[PDB]
Amino acid sequence: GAMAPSYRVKRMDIAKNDEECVVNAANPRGLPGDGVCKAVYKKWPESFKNSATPVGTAKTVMCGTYPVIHAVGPNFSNYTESEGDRELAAAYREVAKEVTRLGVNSVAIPLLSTGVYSGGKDRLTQSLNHLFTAMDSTDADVVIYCRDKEWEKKISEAIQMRT
Ligand SMILES: Cc1cn[nH]c1-c1ccncc1
Ligand SMILES: [Cl-]
Ligand SMILES: [Cl-]
């Protein structure tokens, strides 16, 4: 575990993380995909061997000794708000199980279902709160990755609101 387990946020490409493992915002079929998933495919293509897994689940595949945790959030274009919310919470609980099993001291994680799976809605608070519910009981250093300056500010404020 980390000496003093913490949450941090960085505004940069998750493919350049400084953590002991990465969470992919994967699609269920293990395709190269878009956004975070395409950046992960470019950096760790070997990790896409038999990475297909259902919505609400996480499947880890090693690239060398570096673990890629493929976490499949729901596409809110297809799911109801209610069922989508349940599957999004479930995907993060499966990420916490994998991070724990791997014994890593740190993990790089994107906000699941906030990109092309958001159904055109702002889901920062919804996704981040489900991340906290899952990861609060783990002792890895969690580093959340985002793209946009306004998202970095709101994620940072939410982290500080608890400390
Ligand atoms: C599209 C991309 C590539 N590397 N990281 C991202 C990213 C990460 C977090 N939030 C939005 C985008
Ligand atoms: Cl970057
Ligand atoms: Cl997404």
Image (tube, grey):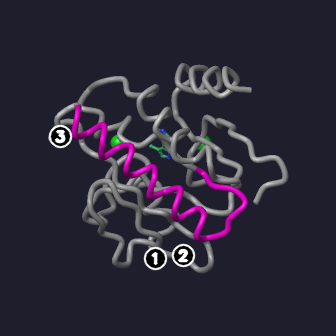
Image quarter in which the C terminus is found: top right
Residue to which mark 1 is pinned: 46
Q: Earlier in the sequence, mark 2 or mark 1?
A: 1
Magenta: predominant secondary structure element? Answer: helix
**Residue 47 placement (x, y as % from top left):** 46, 73
Q: Is mark 1 within 8 Å of ligand 1?
A: no
Is 75 displayed left or right of 123 in the figure? left
- Quadrant for ligand 2 reads top right
Name the kind of residue labelled 2 in the image. Answer: Cys
Front-lying residue, 1 or 151: 1
- Observer-side mark, 2 or 3, equals 3
Residue to which mark 2 is pinned: 63
Secondary structure at numbered mark 3? loop
Q: Residues within 10 Å of mark 1 (few under 14, many from 20)?
A: some
Q: Quadrant of residue 118?
A: top left
Image point 63% across, 55% down: which residue?
A: 107
Residue to which mark 3 is pinned: 79
Asked if the residue under mark 3 is in contact with the one under mark 1, i.e. CB atoms within 8 Å, the reply is: no
Question: CA separation, marks 1 and 3?
Answer: 30 Å
Specify start and end residues of the magenta stretch as a single range.
82-108
Query: Within the magenta stretch, is there residue 97?
Result: yes
Q: Residues within 10 Å of mark 3 (few under 14, many from 20)?
A: few
Question: CA separation, marks 2 and 3?
Answer: 32 Å
Name the kind of residue labelled 3 in the image. Answer: Tyr
